[PDB]
Each structure stands twice: as C-alpha cells, then as structure tokens.
Amino acid sequence: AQSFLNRVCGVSAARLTPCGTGTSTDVVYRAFDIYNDKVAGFAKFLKTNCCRFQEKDEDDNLIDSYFVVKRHTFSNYQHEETIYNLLKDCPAVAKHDFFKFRIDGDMVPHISRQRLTKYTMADLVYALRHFDEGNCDTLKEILVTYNCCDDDYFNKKDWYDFVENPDILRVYANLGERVRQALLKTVQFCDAMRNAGIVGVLTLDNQDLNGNWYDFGDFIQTTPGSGVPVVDSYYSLLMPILTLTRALTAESHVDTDLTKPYIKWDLLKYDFTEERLKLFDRYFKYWDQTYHPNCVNCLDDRCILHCANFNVLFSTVFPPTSFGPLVRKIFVDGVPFVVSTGYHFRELGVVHNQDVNLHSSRLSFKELLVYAADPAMHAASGNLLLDKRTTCFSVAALTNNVAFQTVKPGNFNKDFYDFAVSKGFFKEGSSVELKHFFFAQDGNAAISDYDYYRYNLPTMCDIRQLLFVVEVVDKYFDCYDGGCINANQVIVNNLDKSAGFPFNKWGKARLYYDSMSYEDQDALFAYTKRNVIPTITQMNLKYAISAKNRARTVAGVSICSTMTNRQFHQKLLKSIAATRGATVVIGTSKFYGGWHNMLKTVYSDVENPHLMGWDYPKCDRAMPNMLRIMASLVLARKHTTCCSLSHRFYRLANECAQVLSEMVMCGGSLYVKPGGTSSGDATTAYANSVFNICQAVTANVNALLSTDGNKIADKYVRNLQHRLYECLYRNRDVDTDFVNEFYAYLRKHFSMMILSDDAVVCFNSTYASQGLVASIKNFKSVLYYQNNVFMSEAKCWTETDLTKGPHEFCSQHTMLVKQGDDYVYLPYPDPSRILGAGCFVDDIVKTDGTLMIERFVSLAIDAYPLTKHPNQEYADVFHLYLQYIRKLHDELTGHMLDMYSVMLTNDNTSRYWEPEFYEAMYTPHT
Amino acid sequence: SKMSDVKCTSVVLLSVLQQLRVESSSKLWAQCVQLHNDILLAKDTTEAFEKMVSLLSVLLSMQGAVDINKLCE
Amino acid sequence: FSSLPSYAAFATAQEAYEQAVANGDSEVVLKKLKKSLNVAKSEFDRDAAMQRKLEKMADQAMTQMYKQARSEDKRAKVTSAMQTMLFTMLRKLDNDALNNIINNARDGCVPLNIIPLTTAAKLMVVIPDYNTYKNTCDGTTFTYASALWEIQQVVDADSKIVQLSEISMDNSPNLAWPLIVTALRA
Amino acid sequence: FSSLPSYAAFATAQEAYEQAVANGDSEVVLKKLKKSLNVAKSEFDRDAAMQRKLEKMADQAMTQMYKQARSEDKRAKVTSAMQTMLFTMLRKLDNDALNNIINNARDGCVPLNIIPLTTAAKLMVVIPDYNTYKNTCDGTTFTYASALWEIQQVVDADSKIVQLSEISMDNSPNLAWPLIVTALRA
RNA sequence: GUAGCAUGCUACGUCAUUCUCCUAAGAAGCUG
RNA sequence: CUCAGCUUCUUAGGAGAAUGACGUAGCAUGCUAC
Ligand SMILES: Nc1ncnc2c1ncn2[C@@H]1O[C@H](COP(=O)(O)OP(=O)(O)OP(=O)(O)O)[C@@H](O)[C@H]1O
Ligand SMILES: [Mg+2]
Ligand SMILES: [Zn+2]
Ligand SMILES: [Zn+2]
C-alpha cells in the first residue's frame, strides 16, 4: 500500500495517513443528490467508491482536508482529463491529479483530488434539511470541525431548538461565511465553464465545504463562447440554508468582509433595486429565470413567488429602517400632509401607489379613513422610541409615557368547588385534578408576548419545491368556489368588535361598517386594488383560562384592512366552511354525529391506516414570510376571472402591508413586526390551514425524494418519485397531468383533516415505514428547516389503532362507544378543563350559579361524552354537572319565592338535569 | 386534598390583593403575581404552602386596608 | 287557565253537551250543541292563550329583574366578600405557618416586607408590645411563620438600635414601642 | 282598525243580530243575516289585517329612517373627530427638519422609519434593568441615532420620578424597572 | 225547475295551536 | 379590544307543513214546500 500512498501524495510534500485498509475503498455514507434514468431524488446513498486520505501537518493531527481518490474507467478517465484541462485556470475547482498505477496486472486509472473536506455541501444541506436528534452526528461534526461552536455546546438541553435557546442561531451563522464563499466560487466555476465551452449540471454533492468542485463526469463540450450551467438542482436545494446561516451577512460591511464597519446607507435611500440586481448577479448570476427586484413587474403568482423568495435573502442586507411605508408630502387644501405613497416590502420590493393624489382638493370619509389608518402621521408626529424590552425595531412612541397593562387573576366560584368536594372530587390520588387556571401577569405582559416574534427569522425557502407544493396545495383547494364580492354581499358576524388603532378611539366596527355606505366600501376596495394602504394593528391581551401561563396576545387588525380583506376573501372562506368531507374541516360541527363523520372521512380507504397528528409550536409568530405569502396567493387563485394580474398583486401587497409585516401598536408605541401571520386578519384560520397543508405536502415530497429509490419495489411509486424530481428541479412550468396524479397519490396514501394548526393524518402506515410517504420525522424536519422551529414529543402523536381514534384534535379526545346500536366516535374533553371552567370565571357575576345556569348547561353539553368513559370519575364529572344544575335551579326557585311571592311558572327546564337532553347532541339525526 | 385547595386559596388571595390596589405598585405586584403563578403550577404541597405564606404576608403588610383583628373570625 | 268569564261559558257548554250525550239527542241537536261547544271552547282557548303569553312575558321580565338585582348585589359587595372567602379558606387549610402569622397579625405583629424562603433571608417584623415580644422572642431566636430566625437587628420606633440585654420586664416602658426586628433564616 | 269606518258596518250586523236574535222569529231571515254577519266580520277582519300590516311597515320605516339618521350623525361626528386628530398630529410635526429631510430626498419619498429617527425632538428609552441603563443611557447625555440626547427626566414603572442619582447598581433592586428616560435632542 | 235545510268534497278568507325552515337581536359556552 | 367555526338558551318577525274549528263560492247526493 506504500506505493499507492506515495503515488497519491508524490507531488505534494504533505504527509498521508491511509484511512482505508491498504489501498481499499473506504465505506462512505453521504447525501449524494442523484438523478439517473432509473433513480432520482436527494437521499442518503451508500456510495463506496472513494479512498479518503488525510493530510498530517507538523505536530501530527488530522485537519479537515482529504484526498478523495476514486477509480474510473479509461473512457471516463480521459473525459475527466479533457474537461479538467479546460478548467485548470479557474480557482473555484479542486486541483485534480490524474495518475496511472498498476494494481495487480492492469493499469486501473487512479484519479485523485486534493484539499477536499470530508463532507460536501450536499451533506451540509441534507443534515440541516433532514434533522432528527436521534441521528444528527453529521451536523455535529460539521459544526464542530469548522469552529462554529465548541463540542461541549452539544451537551445542553435542547441545543438544536430555535425556541429553548435562540443562541443556536449564532452557531449557524458561523457557517454563513463558508456558504457565502462556496456560494460565490460556484459562480466562478459557472463563468469558467461558460467561457471554456462546457455544459453540464451543477450538483451540491460535487462541492466541498470550501467551494471547490471535484467532479466532471457529466460534462460535454459545446463550442467556446457557449455553455450553460444548470443550477436549478443546486441553488434550490441550497436555497433555505442561505437564510438559516445568514450567508449574506458579509454584505452589510464595506468591502464585504467580517472585519470592517457596517455600510452606512443614507437614511433617505428607499429604492435598492440596483443593489438587489448587483447581489443577484453576484451570487445567483446563472439563475436561468428572470429575477424582478420589484415584484410589481412580476408576471403571475408563480413569479411573484419566485422573485419574492430572493427578496427575503437580499433584504437581510439593507438597513431595517428603509422598509415600511414610504412617506411623501401631499398638499390638501394647502396644508401639507405626509402620507404613505408606497411601501418598501421586505419581499415584494418597492411598490408605488398607482394614483398618488398630491395637491388634492378635499378629504371625504374614505380619504380620512385611509389617511388615519396608515402610520404615516402616527410615526411622523411621535417621540423617537428605543424600547429595549423588545428586540424588534421600535418606530415611535405616540404618548409621553409608556403604558403597562397587567392581567387579572380570575375570580373563583366557591359554590361549585364546595359542591365538587362534597361529591367526592378534588382529592389526593384522583386522576381528575385542576390544571386550568386564570393566570396573572405583570405590567410587561403585552410587550413580553409580542417579543416572541423574535422566533420569526427571515426565511428563504426552496423555490423549485414550493412552486410545486403550491400547485398541489391548490389542488387540495380545487373543489371550492371563491372570488370577489360586492359590499352588499359581505357577511360579518360581530359588528360590536374593535376597529383597531386609531379607529378604536371613536367607536366599534359597527360605526365604520354602517357609516360608509356600500359605495364607499367598494371604492375603498378598488382603491386597495391599485394602491397600498399600510395600517397599524394593536396587540391586545387575551384574558382566557389555560393550563399554561402564556399571555396569548391577539392582533387587533384595523378596520380599513379587515373590510377589504373580507370583501376579497369572503366567498372563498365561506365555501371552505360550508363544504363537508374535504381535507379542510373548518365549519364542520363536532355534534350530531359530525365527529364520527369526520373520523370516517379521514379513513377514506387507506390501505394500512393508523393515525398521527400535530400542533404547531407557535404558529402565529414562528410562521415564515414566504409561507404566509403563498397562503395569501393560493387563496387568491380563485380570482382568475374577476381580478387582473395587477389587481391581484396589489391585493397581495395590501395583505403584506396590513398583516404580514405591519407596525403594531403594543401599548401606545409603534413597533415593527418581523413577519408571520397576525392572528386577527380576515383569513387567519384558513391561511393557517393552507400553511398546514403546505407543510404536509412538503413532508410528503421530502419523504418521497429522500428515499433511496433502488429498494422501492412499487413500480408506480418509483416512477412517481422519478417524475416528481423532474417536475421539481428540471421542469419549469406547472405540469397538471402530474400535479393531479401526485395529489391523488397523497389523498389515497395520506389522508388529512386540517383545522388551522390542528392536523390529523391517516397515512398508509406500511408505506410510511417503507419511506414512500411523510412520517412524523419528515414533518419534524420540514418544520425545522422551513419554519425554523423544532417540534418535540409534546405536539406530535401516533395512534397505531383506529378503534381508539386520534389522541387529540381541537383538544377533544376521541372514544369509540356503543350508542344507537352502532359504534360511534364521541369527542370527550379534558375533565380538568371542565372543572376549571366551572370553578374559575372571568367576571364576579359568573361565580353566582343562579345567574349563569346556561354556562353549566353548555359545559354539560360539552362534557357529556365523559359519561361513557371507562374511568368512573370521568363520568362523575358529568353527573356532578347535572346535579349542580339541579341545585342551581332549586336555589333559583327558592330565591324567587322568597324575594317575590310568585312561583317560577313553566317547567320545561327539567331536561337540563336529565341525560337525555345531552345525548341528543351526539345523535347523527340532526 | 390540601394540594387542590392551596391553588384556589392563592387565586382568592391574589384577587384580594388586586382589589387593595397593590396592582398600582409594579414591583410588589410583580412579586405577588409571580408567587401566585408559581403556586398554581406547583406539583408539591409544602412549596405551595411557603408561597402561600409569602402571598399572605404581602396581604398582611397592608395593615390599614385590611383589618385582621375583627374580621379574621 | 280558569277564572275568566269565557271559561265559565265553556264549562257550561261542556256540561250541556254531556247532558245531551247522556240523553242521546238527535244528530241535528247533537251538531247544534257540539257547535255551541266548539265556539265557547274557541273563545276560552284564545283568552287562555292570551293569558299564557302575558304570564310568560311577566315571568321573563321578573327573572330579568332578579338577574339585574342579584348581579348588582354581587358587584357591590365584591371587596369584602372576597376577604371573607379568603379567611374562610385560610382557616380551612389550618396550616401551621399561615395560622401562626395570622395570629401574630391579630396582635399587630405584622411583617414589614414579604417573608423570604431562602437561607439568605431578610425578614423584618414589627413588635408593638412586650407581651408579643416575649411570646415570639426568647434570647437570640425568633419564631415566625413556623420558622426560626436569628435576631440580627432590633431598632426602636425612633430608629435607635437597642442592645439585646436592655429589653427586660422592668425596662419595657423605657423603650418607645413598636420595635422592628431584622432577622435571617436559620 | 278600531276606528275604521268599516267597523260601523260590522256594528250594524251585530246590532241586527242582537235585535232579530232577541225576537227569535221569522225563521229564514234569522239564518240569512247570520251569514251576512259572517260577511260583515270577514271583510272587516281582512281590512283590519291590512291596516295592521301598513301600521307595522310604517313603524319599521320610521325606525329605519331614525336608524339611518343616527348613523349619518355618528358618521359626521367621527369625520370631524378624525379631522381634528390629523390636524393635531399635523401641528406636532417639527416642520423645519421634516421639510429639510423631505427636500433632501431624491424624489420627495422617504421611509417612515427614519422620520422619528431624524426629526423627532424627544427620545424615550425604556430600560428593563440596570445593566442596560449603564450600557446605553448612562450619564446625563448620550448618543442614539447620531444625536446628542439630553436626559430630561427618568420615571419608573409606577410613574414615580427617579433622580439620576438613585439609579445605581447597589440601589437598583429598590427601583421599579423598567425605567422610562425621556431624553431631549440637544 | 226555484226557495230553504242536511251529509260529503274542492277552493278561498279567518283564526287555534304543534312542528320545520329561516331573518334579525340578546345571553352564554367550546374550538384554532 | 381581534379573525373565523360550531353549539345551547331567550325574544321578535316571516314563510311553509300538520291537525282542530268558523264563514263564503262551486260540485255530488239526501230532505220540506210548490
Ligand atoms: N383567540 C385567537 N384569536 C385569533 N387567532 C387565534 C386565537 N387563538 C389561536 N389563534 C390562531 O390560531 C393559531 C393557533 O392557536 P393556538 O391556540 O394553538 O396557539 P399556538 O399558537 O398553537 O400556541 P402553542 O402551540 O404554543 O400552545 C394561532 O396560531 C392563531 O393564529
Ligand atoms: Mg398549537
Ligand atoms: Zn418575477
Ligand atoms: Zn378577484
């Protein structure tokens, strides 16, 4: 073996310790992206052909430099020689050494390479894309072998989590430079092999962690002056890492290095189109598709989604004070107003209002509404603010003193607690115990809850994958009828709700829905279809009972935006709510056999079913901007016949300016939302359902493409993945003939039941074990790398038996019971929840049972199913509720008789303390 | 069943404190509210009783507002 | 739904029809009396329906008024009703520490600041009489909240430190009560 | 209706029915006018119903009109109110520096985030603890956003004025963090 | 064949309730 | 102080259906009178 080592390192003076066993191939198990005619996908392949050899420096030790000395046939060897000879000059390439050594009796060509790391960029993207703590040693080695973080940092509890410790981000950023180096050297490679007349496909698995490209077996020579690197399969699998590691962090420094002062961009610079184009031509020069810096010039929703995915990466370079509304000085009646005549979106680029009405004449109700909704004069007349409680940019402080709001403790119903403890409840060792209380918070409640947006990192997403997942997700929404409706066709449940800031100062939403007639509402909706209206959204504090002391703030979005978003999405949302049997079960009641119908729907002919499910850790705040934009797009695909491209883009811009990243008023002070859906917009539940379906489809795609493909014995599935890879990374336009095929495959082997962040799935278990459909590990990985949150074993679950049913959905457990001579699924809630609801109330008057009997009637309606629970105390909960309702009625009758010499007339109320009235709530008749 | 009674007592006591306008003192209100929250999510009984001691002491400090001589009975 | 003038006529018509069927009158007379019945009954039923609707309206108004009155009562006496419940539950718990501190507060021996719980504890108490002082303190130890605290400082009501030996039965009038005792956890 | 002229006709019927029935003679005529009374009643009832319907609609119309009026009035109110707010928040503009920054812009269009950062005459730092206070806001003057901010007043979470000498590492616990320092542009 | 009465039936006006649907309003509960 | 979904209870209005009843028009049959 000495001769082989000498030949390998003959030219290099460096030493060489053989990792292999005497000129024997070393076992290599990496993440080679592959696309052959009989194989496809981006999966961990056991390719054992390289002979890794390491270099030893003085004070013998092994640095991260290896010689990957593999063997090739003579024809491939000659082709590699010719291709390399035309790429020697370029520095973004490995210094190949081609040698001819006899092994036994013939000259097998021993091609070799120099100064190559142990892992490639494919391994880096695979470990960060498919990350399960059960097996993540490759990410450990990558982060420890490049000084990103000390090894001992891996002993921390939840080191990988983006919520338990945000410091993990600081670790990932240490990789960014390397990426941003290998993200630039590739361009050189491209350029070189475009000027050398070489055409081929660039793959991540042919690039080591310092940028060198070390494989030329798949290149053919076109005439010099021509040549096309195909980076669709490279820049798309590497795309989500460029924001996870903040690769373009060395772009805010002069000379673009980490050891120089940040560039001092003039405050007035709002249009960065030129810098965006320079960045695109610098890092993504050979991206085959047209990149529009401003998305107002984009062609279709699949283009507004391509160039917006680059603006989430190029907009992490520009200062955070350049975004938000662009203010211009208009003149009304002579007085100069300052108004938002545009918006510099972090994603949609710079957008200018089509009709900026400077030198106006007079302002009517709609004009005053648009001028008072936007934060132009709110942050133009307001003390500069440096609120250091939040890590989110603070624009201004409207008032002269900060406002601190506390959360009250929640009254206590002594009567019900006495009754329960007199009926044998609330003991030691009982399974049913109080765990739901009205928690209280200090004066930093609202701001501390709003500070949870720090989990909302700026996420760039794999675009070639999202542009297909969006087609499939719309396929899931293909059965609805949606569009734009007039002002007189809008249905609003409560007009007695807040109008948002500053409209909550003068009245409720009723006063702004009735004051301006349908004509003004339609004018305001057609205004948003060609103008961007920024708005302010309070962060109100929610007073609700829970088993955790989270504050649960909710965005009180402004009326000027809620009106228009309703007028835009109402038909589609109502059509989503009013259809039964669909994947989205919003609007489907759990009573009158609805739960059983849903459960049997999820089981729609799944070959080997057994369910799983999930609850996003923090959906509202952790949601990325790209996924929210995609949700707002696929909910606007129903307007193909009513709204043009420009109108739909301006509606997307309005939605982004009013929901996605809008400056909130969290206690008399304007802040800046990093991103993510606000939990007060007109499409919160349905947008969450869209995002959930998108994550599920992405998990399916990653599980079907991350399979080896050689061991798939189902020909149809093998070809399904072989065409899925083509439709993702080779095809460019929507392929309906395969989009519907894959949608059918999912709906067959992967059932779903989506209600916002609640998801129940009835995947075909045998396939999931095989790897042909999304398991729960796949969903965890997808959430990790796309949604930049880690999902632990407290939101997931998996029920191997259908009879028991889903472990939880909407916090209601499921049980199979014999009622009506047929086994039916009944949802029983958590008994502790019901006892807590009874014992603890919001208002002091709710602690007097006689006043609130309907409270207990409704609580018994919700708690009846426990009566059939095997545990005796679970049924005792419902029986106790019935007895307490009877006791309350007796007390009410006695009080009426004593206070007034009149007896309570009519006795229709005898139903409430008899179980018949509550079994009728789960009989499928009505 | 004292474990499930200290939590209700803590809720009642924090309500009583909030009625005494201890909420208009951010530092003391933060102390008492954190004590109450820790009492609620307590799986032990003795620890909840020590936090109950502290909360009741918060109530006792306000001698003027609460007369515990003739209304303790 | 009786006591109305229509029900009397209806009952008389019922009695007349009963007498007719007893006599087995002819079908023509039977029909005539049956229609006299049906008209009297049709009047009484209408009147009784009016009475029933009026009564249901009155009952709903009365119960709404009762709701209003009891809600106003519940809101009015909300402060004292919460303290009574608090002390009832405190007595029910019957813990040693809570009972001890409540008894001390009965005599006025309140704490100046929250009672700490750690070894590095700073507890300040007010001792307004020598009776409570001797009951609670004996030497250089202090009993409070079922806890032992070491007397670190004992300052009079005029901010003057007092040597421990000075406080005696014969020296009690000399000191200006109350005392303030600062102690640590033992 | 009760006063409707058709009532008179009905009355006549009843009057005749109250007269001829008293006589109880002439046979056929008694049977005839009874039907006429049924004719007298029916139409009258019908007319009554019609009138009642009209009355109901009239009431509804009035209510609707009244409702509209209220809305209009409220609309106007808000309009005026909203105008006032704008005017107020228009006058608080530091129009000198605001006009300077607008004119210095390339096309009169500048971000909103830089308006407070460049024309605001008062900074207001909310400091959650003391380490942050000494890091950023220390001294009687400091620098934020390239300006010389003069600390004008420090208040705590209770709105209690805090003298700059009270903010110390040793004395920090006894303060009610956060602190709201309302600096001023020099 | 006309007048009157009786039984039945079809249609319309009138009411009596019961049920269903729904238009709106109020109170409350649960779900993401 | 939010955005949607479902459920219970209460009140008012409208329509329809079921049964009970009155009145009128028409048809079948029966009866008194000429
Ligand atoms: N009261 C609400 N108002 C509006 N939206 C809500 C409300 N509660 C929940 N949501 C919306 O539903 C989604 C999830 O609600 P959920 O109650 O599960 O909170 P969560 O954010 O999932 O918190 P966690 O999972 O950590 O308990 C939220 O993401 C929010 O957008
Ligand atoms: Mg959740
Ligand atoms: Zn485009
Ligand atoms: Zn449309």
Image (cartoon, coloured by chain):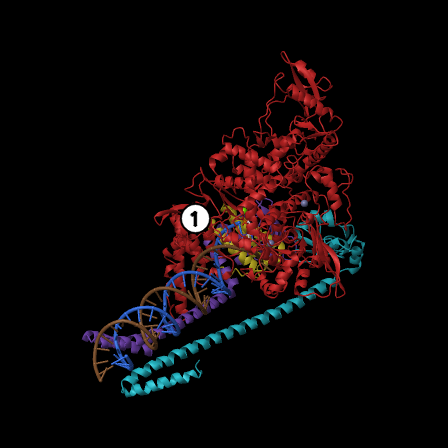
Chain colours: A red, B yellow, C purple, D cyan, E blue, F brown
Q: In terms of depth relative to the viewer, which is nearer, A727 or A446?
A: A727
Question: Which one is in front, A450 or A745?
Answer: A745
Is A49 left, or right, of D184 in this rendering? left
Q: Is residue B22 left or right of residue D94?
A: left
- Percent across and percent down for residue A178 are 70, 33
Quarter placement of the C terminus of chain A: bottom left
Disc 1 residue: CB within 8 Å of ligand 1: no
Q: Does F33 appear above or below A315?
A: below
Q: Residue A727, located in which quarter of the rendered image?
A: top right
Amino acid at the residue labelled 1: Asn
Relative to residue A525, is residue A733 depicted above or below? above
Question: Looking at the image, which residue is at 61% across and 33% down?
Answer: A126
- For image coordinates 57% across by 54% down, the residue present is A483
Q: Decide: is A701 above or below A510.
A: above
The residue sitting at the left extreme is: C23
Count of numbered badges drawn on the protein? 1
The residue at which mark 1 appears reads as: A597
Local packing at callout 1 (Cα closer than 10 Å; few below 14, some 14-19, many 20+) is: some
Residue positioned most to the top? A105
SS category of the residue bearing label 1: helix
- The image position of residue A225, as x and y in percent, is 75, 32
Q: Position of residue F7 (x, y in %)?
A: 44, 56
Residue in front for this viewpoint, A176 or A38: A38
The quarter of the picture where residue A254 lies is top right
Give the answer, above or below, for where D7 lies relative to A663. below
Q: Is residue D125 visible?
A: no
Q: Is residue A91 visible to the viewer in this orientation of the structure?
A: yes
